[PDB]
Length: 131
Image (cartoon, rainbow, N blue to C red):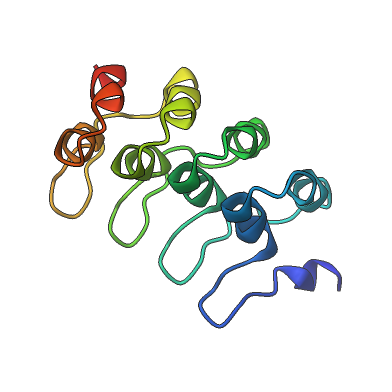
């Protein structure tokens, strides 16, 4: 009952996501290598991969991908990991995402494309990357 460690925080955060979000080097493989639900989501509908994107933890984004992470996963706001990458400006990580064929055409709840949020949030290099 050690898989019961898909234990969450009050807000749905799990160990993997912490690891992603906090970019803690080993626990990602530990958690993934221990068969941690790689598509677990916090109350907001965010996966490790999202969270890794948001913070641009390329490494994490890398491995999570390498191990079955739903790359086109949408959160409550329908924002995929790629999307947040832009919005926040995870250049390196958006590369990673597209390099894996992430659908740059999926839009959030306001029909905004990952390009619209990079453009808007003036993350120019992501704008062109998306192009």
